[PDB]
Amino acid sequence: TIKEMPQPKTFGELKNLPLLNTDKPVQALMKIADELGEIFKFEAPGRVTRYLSSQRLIKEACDESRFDKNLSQALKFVRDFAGDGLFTSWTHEKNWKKAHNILLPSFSQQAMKGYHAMMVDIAVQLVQKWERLNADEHIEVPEDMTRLTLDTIGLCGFNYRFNSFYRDQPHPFITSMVRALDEAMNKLQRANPDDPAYDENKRQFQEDIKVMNDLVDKIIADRKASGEQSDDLLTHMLNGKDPETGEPLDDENIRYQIITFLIAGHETTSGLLSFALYFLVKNPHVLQKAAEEAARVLVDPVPSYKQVKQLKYVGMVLNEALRLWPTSPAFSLYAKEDTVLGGEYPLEKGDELMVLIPQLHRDKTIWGDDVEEFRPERFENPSAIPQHAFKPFGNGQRACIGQQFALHEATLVLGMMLKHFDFEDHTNYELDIKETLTLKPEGFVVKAKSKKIPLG
Ligand code: HEM
């Protein structure tokens, strides 16, 4: 019984594109979803996709025998500097499976034991920065979380120190990377890209790509020359061999993986830490519960890997922040073969689907009617959550390879913040979600009063 699907307002030849001509497209899509339901068609010039919001349909979309990851236009633009790294490659590209096989072990929960010391190094820098603020000062949350995540990924990724806490202006690589990502995201909403008015953007874009490649290529070359072995991903990549073929990743691909870790993990993880602190200061009883656990568990001057694993409630707080505002809000899929979705929507080979994660996470048939409330206790027993109901890290073999790294980092840092400071929402901050490739609470600021507990 084929059902025709909904579609928002069209604009002649422009189709639906004008509707995303806003600074907050995902939040706009969420409203369209509220209006049209679990599935709606969305067209742009020369493009068509279908946005899914219900767990019932998304669970079918997550069947890998039927759908595979699609490279959205955003990922195609990011590929200009992320290359055939894991995030911007097709599943069928030789280098995707090769890098996946080599890197998977280096990203397991067990492997986090090896990155822990480096994560603690940067976390201690963040805590010390806040301990050193004077009384009249405050904290710019996303800004400091981003300094932390970029530096942590640089240190664990290739033993390089961006030293973000020593600067007002970021290290040149960071400025170039951030500018390159911004340019890639800006191309999504510029009709006449060839307009000479964009010749300066193109020149700057090529310059930024060169800054990124030059630094990373240099570090790879310096490492191969010295023969030094470290606890970073670069050592794993220089020494790894794909079990299927016996081939190692070549230097160019290693460079793209390094750039990819920074691109894929810096903003998503800092956004998660920022949203989590936002929900905590807005819900004092929850912050109190989380602070009590941190004080009980983190009994040493420096957290150990095992202690971070015991911060169960902090982990629930992070999952609930990811439920409400998953920081990489949507992912794209294509139909591998002709198929019918949900018994009513026929699809043809190659047809695209978009999983709208914030909406999936607000499916009342799964979570209950109080979906807008921040309640970490929803994650008390993970086994009760239906398959494919909670997907902040994507799906299947193309799910986030950095999930254990991101959660270890976030749990460690949030635990240390809760152990060391009391927090004040001194401006009664009004949530304003800024959208780029990711989501974050723009302008979120707080004041942190030290509990004066030694940090080893
Ligand atoms: C809470 C923070 C994070 C979130 C929410 C997140 C989310 C995601 C999502 C949704 C995908 C799937 C994208 C798609 O289907 O197109 C993904 C892929 C990926 N993420 Fe993350 N991520 C986070 C942190 C990280 C970190 C810290 C790293 C690096 C240490 C990382 C590395 C990657 C890579 C390499 C892929 C592509 C994997 C593959 O396709 O083989 N992510 N991530």
Image (cartoon, helix red, strand yellow):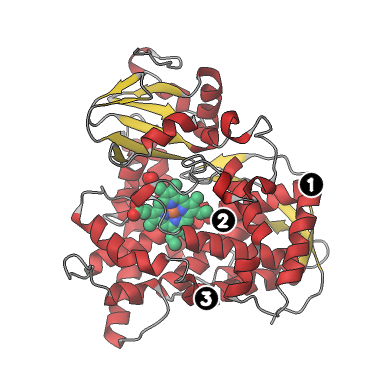
Q: Earlier in the sequence, mark 3 or mark 2?
A: 3
Quadrant (top left/top right/bottom left/bottom right) for the C terminus? bottom right
Vertical relation: 22 (above or below) 242: above
Of badges 3 and 1, nearer the viewer stands: 3
How many residues crowd mark 1 within 10 Å: few (<14), some (14–19), many (20+)?
few
The residue that mark 1 highlights is 427
Q: CA distance from mark 3 to mark 1?
A: 34 Å
- Please identify the quarter of the rendering in which residue 226 is found: bottom left
Secondary element at image label 2: helix
Q: Is residue 172 left or right of residue 45?
A: right
Q: Is residue 262 visible?
A: no
- Please tell me which residue lies in front, 282 or 159: 282
The residue that mark 2 highlights is 270
Residue 139 percent coordinates (x, y): 71, 58
Q: Amino acid at mark 1?
A: Thr
Q: Is residue 453 left or right of residue 20?
A: right
Q: Is residue 303 visible?
A: yes
Q: CA distance from mark 2 to mark 1?
A: 21 Å
- Check contact, mark 3 vs mark 2: CB within 8 A: no
- The residue at the point 78 percent across, 63 percent down is 292
Secondary element at image label 1: loop
Q: Earlier in the sequence, mark 2 or mark 1?
A: 2
Query: Disc 2 beta carbon < 8 A from ligand 1?
Result: no
The residue that mark 3 highlights is 118
Residue 451 percent coordinates (x, y): 82, 70
Of badges 2 and 1, nearer the viewer stands: 2
- Please tell me which residue lies in front, 204 or 387: 387
